Image (cartoon, coloured by chain):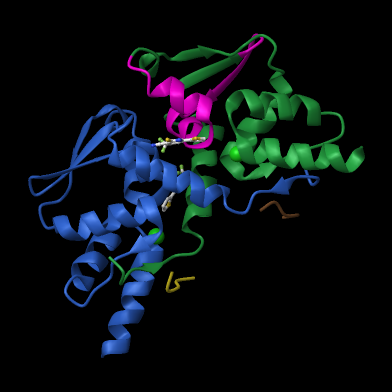
Chain colours: A brown, B yellow, C green, D blue
Amino acid sequence: AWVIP
Amino acid sequence: AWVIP
Amino acid sequence: ADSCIQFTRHASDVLLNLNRLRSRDILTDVVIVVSREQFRAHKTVLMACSGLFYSIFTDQLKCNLSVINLDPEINPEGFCILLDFMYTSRLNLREGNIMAVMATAMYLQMEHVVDTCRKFIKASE
Amino acid sequence: ADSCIQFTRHASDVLLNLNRLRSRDILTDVVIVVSREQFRAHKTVLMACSGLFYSIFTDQLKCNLSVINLDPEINPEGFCILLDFMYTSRLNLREGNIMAVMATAMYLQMEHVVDTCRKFIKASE
Ligand SMILES: [Cl-]
Ligand SMILES: [Cl-]
């Protein structure tokens, strides 16, 4: 996997 | 984009 | 073949176009009903994202249904957030919805979402 | 929302599962016929990848067809390579098939494939 897009 | 996977 | 080249952006462009089809209501083939809230979707996208929908639409009788009613305990906003995630890879996870999103992801059998929800909850405990 | 988190692998996992559905012939809803070779596929994936199929399946009459016959000049192997690319992001581009793949991609309106074909041809000239 999860990220800040 | 195109790459060698 | 081991001689293939790969277009990096292809899978995300396909997903972006499937979402466009959903917004324009093109070739949607099922209505998911969540406590009287209705959501139109594509069965193949639901099956590709959710273990529950994979089980539903591979059943010889349910594969033909045009309406699927979810358990009344499922929160419609939680389902909406998960359906948006299926079509975009983006999860609108907030303090006010995390419990509903986690419970909905457990029911839909969306393990990566359950995992991030557990991590965010553990961080706040 | 601007507060979303994103699962990087989601779009490729969705595409991998749509390909699995295609291999198992699950919920395929159209047969594409190319010089008597038949290919089963999902209309939504075809529309998401090809400008030609987007135009076809948004037509009020053709959207309902279960068989689509392509122009007899289209090479079945070229179509097969492009259909595999639609479902996997991988293009099996070889000296022996590049002209057929390029011509098929021009017909299907798959501009990124046309572009790489032009580059590979230009490199060999
Ligand atoms: Cl997931
Ligand atoms: Cl393309």
Asked whether residue C23 is drawn in magenta, I would say no
Q: Using the image, determine if residue C31 lies above or below residue D112.
A: above
Is C117 or A5 nearer to us in this picture? C117
Rendered-image quarter of ligand 2: bottom left
D35 relative to C3 in the view: left or right: left
Position of the N terminus of chain C, as image quadrant, is: bottom left
Q: Residue furthest left?
A: D36
C35 relative to D67 in the view: left or right: right
Q: Position of residue C101 (x, y in %)?
A: 73, 29
Q: Using the image, determine if residue C2 lies above or below residue D89.
A: below
Res. D50 in view: no
Quarter residue D117 falls in: bottom left
Q: Using the image, determine if residue C88 lies above or below residue C36.
A: below
- Residue drawn at (46%, 29%) of the image: C42
Q: Position of residue D98 (x, y in %)?
A: 23, 72
C121 relative to D75 in the view: left or right: right
Q: Position of residue C108 (x, y in %)?
A: 59, 26
- Residue drawn at (43%, 32%) of the image: C44
Q: Using the image, determine if residue C110 lies above or below residue C88.
A: above
Res. D124 in view: yes
Quarter residue C29 falls in: top left
Give the mark count: 0
Residue range in magenta is C34-60
Q: Position of residue D99 (x, y in %)?
A: 20, 72
- Residue drawn at (50%, 47%) of the image: D13
Position of the C terminus of chain C, as image quadrant, is: top right
Q: Residue furthest right?
A: C125
Is C104 or D109 nearer to us in this picture? C104
